[PDB]
Image (spheres, coloured by chain):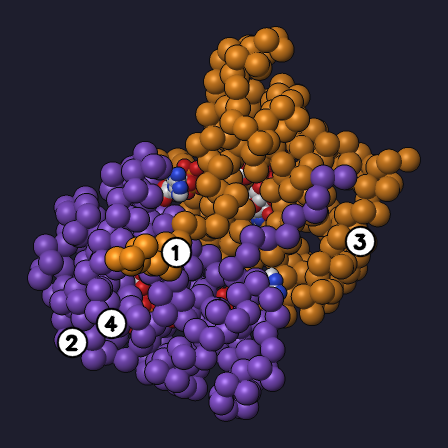
Chain colours: A purple, B orange
Amino acid sequence: KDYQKLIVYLCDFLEKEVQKRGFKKVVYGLSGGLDSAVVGVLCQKVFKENAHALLMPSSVSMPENKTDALNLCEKFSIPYTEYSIAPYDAIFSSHFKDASLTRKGNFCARLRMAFLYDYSLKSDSLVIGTSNKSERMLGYGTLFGDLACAINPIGELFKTEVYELARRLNIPKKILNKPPSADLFVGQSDEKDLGYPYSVIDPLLKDIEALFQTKPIDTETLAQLGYDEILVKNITSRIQKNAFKLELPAIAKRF
Amino acid sequence: KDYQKLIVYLCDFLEKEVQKRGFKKVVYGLSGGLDSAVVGVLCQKVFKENAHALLMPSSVSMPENKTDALNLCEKFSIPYTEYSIAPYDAIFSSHFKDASLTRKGNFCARLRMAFLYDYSLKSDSLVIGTSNKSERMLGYGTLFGDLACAINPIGELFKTEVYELARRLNIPKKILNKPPSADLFVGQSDEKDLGYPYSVIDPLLKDIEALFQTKPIDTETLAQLGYDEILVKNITSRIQKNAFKLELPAIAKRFNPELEHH
Ligand SMILES: Nc1ncnc2c1ncn2[C@@H]1O[C@H](COP(=O)(O)OP(=O)(O)OC[C@H]2OC([n+]3cccc(C(=O)O)c3)[C@H](O)[C@@H]2O)[C@@H](O)[C@H]1O
Ligand SMILES: Nc1ncnc2c1ncn2[C@@H]1O[C@H](COP(=O)(O)OP(=O)(O)OC[C@H]2O[C@@H]([n+]3cccc(C(=O)O)c3)[C@H](O)[C@@H]2O)[C@@H](O)[C@H]1O
Ligand SMILES: Nc1ncnc2c1ncn2[C@@H]1O[C@H](COP(=O)(O)OP(=O)(O)OP(=O)(O)O)[C@@H](O)[C@H]1O
Ligand SMILES: Nc1ncnc2c1ncn2[C@@H]1O[C@H](COP(=O)(O)OP(=O)(O)OP(=O)(O)O)[C@@H](O)[C@H]1O
Ligand SMILES: [Mg+2]
Ligand SMILES: [Mg+2]
């Protein structure tokens, strides 16, 4: 129950990493969801007015999410800026009508990466990421999109742990009770895309991280732990298919 | 010859890296410049028609560059597609009229990454990078922009070496002698931005690679070699300031509390 210890640890991390790089200001995307709310509150405790939230709704971003984001900023005195990327996704939709929801969402996530980095350069700030360990392991995120940042304080925290941390940070119940959703298209949700809730995925991901962090996953070993055959096959496939997102691009060694 | 061994080496790298990932098709951005022309020719030899070139001119892109890129595809039978990003940068210019040239250029480089990746997903392909070793060490490129890719065959070749390889690959003279330029704004050139041509930069980078790799750069040692003080200061700064572009993000490790009995 020593989450106060964890909060101090993460705040110290943010302070040290930003300082060692020669910066004193940070920016991050605030979506109205749990993860970015946690990152926003942590940065506010460390940089106060020097931590800035950037809200970037799209043409399909759900309205409620944005208002919840604004309410968070007012509650925690977080300076913010609202910048719509709708004019950009509108062009993409007109040029690629039959584009899959995934392609449309990935473009938006990258547009967000671009404006966060643009904002950072013009204001001399660093971009703080919000991807949690569950998403990172599953590769549930857009490469060079929401996975793009300079520093990420909750990258080794599983989704269930980010939630527990959020409670200690007094994150609004509105955001705490909100089901995870990339919000890249109307009706999207982590549970629907993944097929299982984080209450079922996280326990398995934790054993996989402990047993096979730098070695191949042994589905038979996981089977012995009492995990559903189908569940293991599905989660293992996702992890192995997206392992590349956690690695640097392959560069031919000097001849 | 060693250049032929190099070509075979790079071709094998591309085929093995793409195959081990379960792919058979690749895509890359063709700007009309030397770096992308080199990557395009190499990919054509390995994947033939399965290697696609994506031309993405902006509102400021020089027209001559697109023409040279198109002629390259014709000479080497490279399938291509032209998608202008002008409509997108036009909105950016309208929203941020006073944005710096660097900010505007970074936005375009990132739009190109997004379309290359969009194209790769819809066609079951991998994005091949074109950043050379000089650009990588100097951080002369947009993070998550042109530096973004799955595999990069020329990341360990200095610009000067890329030029020599290009000669053996029979790249059009128009491209070979073309001055390096991000072409993110009218009149841009690597020499004007960096302050020096690669003929002066590369020799210094090669010494830095040989002298410093386990320890930080020592400007006094470089001064003893005979390098000009300004060149050393300029290049050393670019390398140290932009080293972060070649690394993954800093992620906070799991918290391990120091227990009372520890
Ligand atoms: N083996 C390999 N080695 C190196 N590169 C490889 C590769 N295999 C594919 N690639 C490349 O990776 C690309 C596919 O990766 P990527 O573009 O990320 O795309 P993808 O993984 O296909 O889509 C991202 C997914 O996670 C999503 N997401 C996005 C944003 C936020 C959240 C959230 O929960 O907040 C979730 C999204 O909705 C979708 O379900 C390919 O098209 C290809 O260019
Ligand atoms: N220490 C650090 N650790 C982690 N992240 C750090 C950081 N310092 C800055 N950052 C972040 O990195 C950002 C700055 O990097 P970045 O956005 O790339 O921007 P930046 O390096 O400032 O501009 C890109 C540069 O490379 C150029 N370029 C671009 C595109 C193509 C070519 C070409 O030759 O084709 C050359 C360009 O002309 C310019 O000289 C910052 O705003 C910040 O968010
Ligand atoms: N409309 C948006 N405005 C600003 N940032 C956004 C927006 N949509 C996505 N982002 C950014 O991309 C990330 C993707 O959201 P993600 O679903 O992963 O987490 P979240 O919304 O913070 O929390 P949760 O996973 O519970 O929904 C956000 O954390 C945020 O940094
Ligand atoms: N108009 C464009 N169309 C397609 N791709 C582009 C365009 N502009 C830039 N790119 C991509 O981004 C990269 C920019 O890198 P860069 O300008 O340094 O190299 P280059 O133009 O190939 O060669 P050079 O360094 O001599 O200019 C290109 O290699 C290419 O993949
Ligand atoms: Mg969300
Ligand atoms: Mg060029």
Seen at 14% across and 46% down, the residue is A49
Does residue A43 appear to the left or right of B147 in the view shown?
Answer: left
Give the residue number, with chain letter if any, for mark 4. Answer: A164
Residue mark closest to the camera, 3 vs 4: 4
- What is the C-alpha distance between the residues marked 1 and 2? 29 Å
How far across and down, in percent of the image, does residue B5 sit? 86, 42
**Label 3 secondary element:** helix
Q: How packed is label 1: few (under 14 Cα within 10 Å), some, or many (20 or more)?
A: some
Q: Quadrant of ligand 2?
A: top left
Seen at 17% across and 52% down, the residue is A44
Give the residue number, with chain letter if any, for mark 3. Answer: B12
Instruction: Check the image and report above or below for A199 versus B148.
Output: below
Outermost residue toward the front?
A: B261
**Numbered badge on residue B62:** none
- The chain containing the residue under callout 3 comes to B
- The chain containing the residue under callout 4 comes to A
Please, what is the three-letter code of the amino acid marked with disc 2?
Answer: Lys
Callouts 4 and 1 close, C-beta under 8 Å: no
Q: How packed is label 3: few (under 14 Cα within 10 Å), some, or many (20 or more)?
A: some
**Label 1 secondary element:** loop
Instruction: Check the image and report above or below for B256 versus A59.
Output: above
Of A159 and B239, nearer the camera is A159
Seen at 35% across and 83% down, the residue is A199
Please, what is the three-letter code of the amino acid marked with disc 3?
Answer: Asp
Mark closer to the chain start, 2 or 4? 4
Give the residue number, with chain letter if any, for mark 2. Answer: A174
Give the residue number, with chain letter if any, for mark 1. Answer: B253
Callouts 3 and 4 close, C-beta under 8 Å: no
- What is the C-alpha distance between the residues marked 3 and 1? 37 Å
Of A37 and B58, nearer the camera is A37
Task: Establish whether labels 4 and 1 are both on one chain.
Answer: no
Callouts 2 and 4 close, C-beta under 8 Å: no
